Each structure stands twice: as structure tokens, then as C-alpha cells.
Length: 355
Image (tube, rainbow, N blue to C red; front, side, top):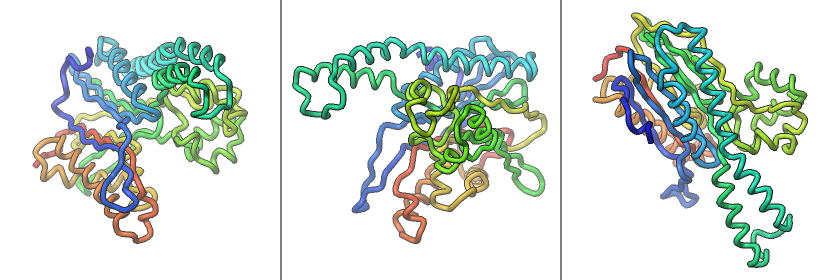
């Protein structure tokens, strides 16, 4: 890739771990291929790009997004002179192009799929479909993998000490400021879910019954109400009860862009993390505990570790043992930790002391 080619940011570190399901007769785990990803890039005249992505239904979309977002932001589209309004524009455009070009990229395969299904008798067994139809089924399996996938993303750009955050979904960005009273933690973006009132509003404005969706709180295995890709919800929502009423795409790919944070004289760090990381902590420790806890865990590791990568990885490791132990013991919460998802934690340092 042309991504694999240039400047990594030395002021950031990443830690990660793959999804895991704990074995029934406990001693061993199971994992599906990981679907998280990230990026930490520094381009000319000091503008930085960081992102953490959470995919589902394969990792093709998370890679497509990482790759394309880069292409749309690090080849000159940016330069610290633009000022908020412009940078927001550029971010909004980069996300639009990523979504559109992604949908365009699977159009052919979609048509070929329709054409193959047309040749297949419907509602007939995985098996017991004359072997004559097997070559078709296979080709359909191959296309399904090509077209499948969705991804949530949280991206942050650093344009001349001003920090911008673009978010689509439920990954999170936390600004951890070291003061004199301790560490102040503020989540820069908002989780796009049924619990998000503004998202619930948007959804009702489309003709969906907010009441029922708010109650179920999850749309086809995913909580995020904003996602990139996923042909299933972008095109077949009318065919999904919970959304069947939408008069417009209920799940959108538009990013919510946040403020513009000044970083002159601030000391601390930025955290970008995937949904699997915090959902594992809260599954072990309970509702709403994650931001504070993770920031503290990171604070702690900052004193021991010798790299930002070790810092981030130590925290990820800590969260999985907490989760693993919780399941392993059996005191209530165990029922909540039968498995966990991919975890990614990127830390961008802002003068905070490192061991």
C-alpha cells in the first residue's frame, strides 16, 4: 500500500488485542478474525492524523476506510492555515467520499449477486441443493465476502496545535488534561446510539418509532446508529422490521465533527479507543465506569512504561485480565463477561511525562 510507505508519528502509541470468547470448560479461548484498526500519521508542516476503527462483518471496510481517509486527508487536502470552518469542510468531504466510493466499489458485485440468486431456487437448504447448484453457491459466498462489512470510526486531526475530532459511531476520543487537582477527563465525541437523544430525534424525523428502537437499543447486532459501509443497512433497511418504516437511510455515514480544541500550554494526552475496549470494562465493572477508569489506568502506566505503545498495550492487557478474571471467578458480573470484542487503544501524548 501507499499507506505503508510514509511518516509515523513518534508522539503516539497503540495497544490492541483481538476479540475472545471464553471456553465453556474454561481453559482456552476462541477468536474470529480481528476487525479493529487504526492509524497514526504525521504529514508535512505538522498536521497529524489519528484514527481508531471498529469493523464488523469482516474487516474489509475498516481497511478500505483507513486507506481512503488517508488518501483524502494526507495528500495536501490539509494544511494549518485553513481554520476550523475549512478543516471541518475537508473532514466532512473526506468522509463523504469514503462512503460513496465504498458503495460504488461493491455495485458490480451486488448486481452479479442478484443475477446469481435469480438462478437459484429460493428458500432451499444449505445442503440438499443439487450439486449442480454448488458452483453458484460458492460464487455467491465469494461475493458475499467481497461486499460485506461496516465500520465505525473516530478520527482526530491535529492542525497546528488545534485538535479536531470526527466521529461516526461508538468509538471514543478522550482528552485527558493534567491540572493541579488531578487529571480531567472529557469525552470529545458522543456515542451514536439509541441512547443518544439527538440520534433518537433524527431517527423519528425519518418516520421510525423512537419508542421501540430506543427500547431494543441495538440494530442488527450493532448499537451504533451511524456507520460507514454495510450494504445491508444502507440498501436493505426497508426490509428490517426495526427500520422498515424509515423514509430515508436510518443509519448514516456522516461524521459529527467536534469543536476545535486549542492545545497550547495543555499537558496530558488524547485517547482514541474502540467500542470493544470500554464495553469490556463496563461489562466487568458496571455501567458508565470506563472513561474514568481507562484514563486512570493510562495515567498509572505512563509512570512505568518506556514507550507509548507499552503504555497503551499495558492498559489493554489490564482490561482483558479484569474481564477474564471476572468471568473466571463467578461473582454475579461473570454472566456479563462470557466473551469480549476487539480492543484498540491509541494514545497521543501532549507533554505528559513518561516513566
